[PDB]
Image (cartoon, rainbow over all chains, first blue to last red; front, side, top):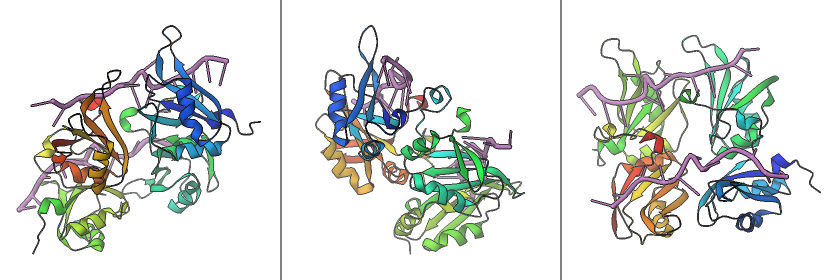
Length: 181
Length: 181
RNA sequence: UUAGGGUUAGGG
RNA sequence: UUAGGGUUAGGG
C-alpha cells in the first residue's frame, strides 16, 4: 500500500561501516518509520560490504523525519544519508556531490531576490540569494545562485530539474565550482 | 583605548565589489560598532581594487555581532568576511580555506565524544564528533574530527593552535581533505 | 538560450 | 608523536 513512489522514499546510506548488515541497518533506521526495503550492497564474489546501502520508508514523511535525525551513527560510525538519485542523473557529473548551493538558469532579467526567496523558501532555510549581473554594465545575466543551510534541501530540489519561477521555466542544477567543470 | 588585540578585532573582507571604497566599506560595517581601521586593498600602480579589504572594530564583541549579521551585501555584492589570519599562518597551507571541520590531534586513547563536546561547545554549535579508531582492531588512534554548523566557529578556534582537552595538550588544525595534502 | 570575479590575505 | 575508509550510487 505505498502511495508515494520508490525513489522519493529511498535513501542512499554511504560510508557504512563494513560490520553493517541488512539487519543492523534496519534495526537503526526503523526508529523513524517502517522500512519497505533495506539492503547493504556487497560484492558478488567476496560478499564483503561495499560501504553503502539503501533504505526505503513507507512514507516520505518518515524519510524527512529520518533526515531530521542527522547525524546517524550506525554500528559505531557516522554515515552520510542522501536522497536517492535516479540511475539517470547518477551518470551526470556532480549528482552525488554534497552541496548547499544550486544553479537557477532561465530567470530572464526580471526576477529579483524576493522571487527566488518566496519560491525556494518552501524547500528549506535560505542562506544567500545571488542574482548574477554583469559588472559595470549592471545588466542581469538571467541566472542566480541560491544557498541553503542544509544540503538535503538542495537534494530534494535537484531531483526535479524543472521549476516554474516568476513565470519562467527554469532549470535547477547543483552548484559546481569552476574546478569541477 | 583598545583592550583586545588588533588581529582578534580585525576581519578580512574578501570578494569586495570593485566599486567598494574605504568609505562605502566603512559605511556598511559601522552598523555593528565603531571601526578602528577600515581599508580597501588596491594595486599600488593602478589603484584598482584587489577584491578584498580589512575592517577592525573596537571590541571583539562588535566583531562577533558583525559575524552574526551574515550574509553581508556591500555595494550590491555578497562578501565573505573571515577572522583575520596571522601573516604567519597565512603562509601555511589551507589557512584561508572555509571549512566547518577541525582536526584534533593528541587526545591520547582515553578521550571520548563527551570530552570533545563539553570542551568545543564553548565555540559554537557542534554537528558531528568523530573519534577516529582503527577498524577491526577497535584501538583509538589518538585524534578526532569535530564538525560545526558555522565556519566562523572553526576560524575562531584555529587561531589558537594549542588547546588542553581532557588533560592533554592537543593541536587543532583545519580539516583538509586527502586531495589537499 | 541557463555557470560565479578565488587578486577572496596586509596597506598602515 | 597528532590526517579520515570517497567502493560513499542500485541488489531486487
